[PDB]
Image: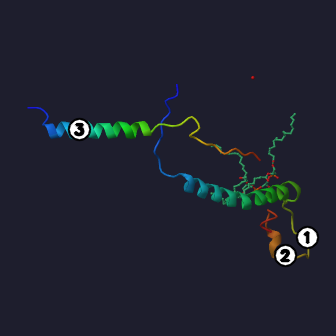
Amino acid sequence: SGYTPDEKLRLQQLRELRRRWLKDQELSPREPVLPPRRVT
Amino acid sequence: HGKRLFIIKPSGFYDRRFLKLMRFYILLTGIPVAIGITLVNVFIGEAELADIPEGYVPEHWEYFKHPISR
């Protein structure tokens, strides 16, 4: 019962990649570059 | 707190552009039409019914009320 070593290794690699991707999903402070223009 | 994330969504640029084009053209024609209708109604319209003068035959467009219809 429990994880096999291959399962543990694959899970650890997949979660490391997932955490890297999720961290990459964040935004920089200047990330939404908005172009400005006006016409009681 | 600075924990802003990226929201994955389809490109709404094309839909917004199409809606803007539709609104632009529809207004481009409607606004002059609405202005003309308002001016005609306030300055020209509202004909009033009258009895036909004796011996005078009216034109085929003299039997209608609204000036645009005439």
Number of labels in the image equals: 3
**Chain for numbered disc 1:** B
Quarter of the image with the C terminus of chain A in it:
top right
The label nearer to you, 3 versus 1, is: 3
Q: Residue B59 carries which label?
A: 2
Residue B37: x and y, percent?
79, 58
The label nearer to you, 2 versus 1, is: 2
Q: Distance between the Cα atoms at labels 3 and 1? A: 100 Å
**Chain for numbered disc 3:** A
Whether the residues at callouts 3 and 1 have beta carbons within 8 Å, the answer is no
Task: Please tell me which residue is depicted at 35% across the width and 36% down the height of the picture.
Answer: A19
Q: Mark 1 points at which residue?
A: B53
Task: Please tell me which residue is depicted at 87% across the width and 59% down the height of the picture.
Answer: B44
Q: Distance between the Cα atoms at labels 2 and 1? A: 13 Å
**Chain for numbered disc 2:** B
- Relative depth, front residue between B18 and A21: A21
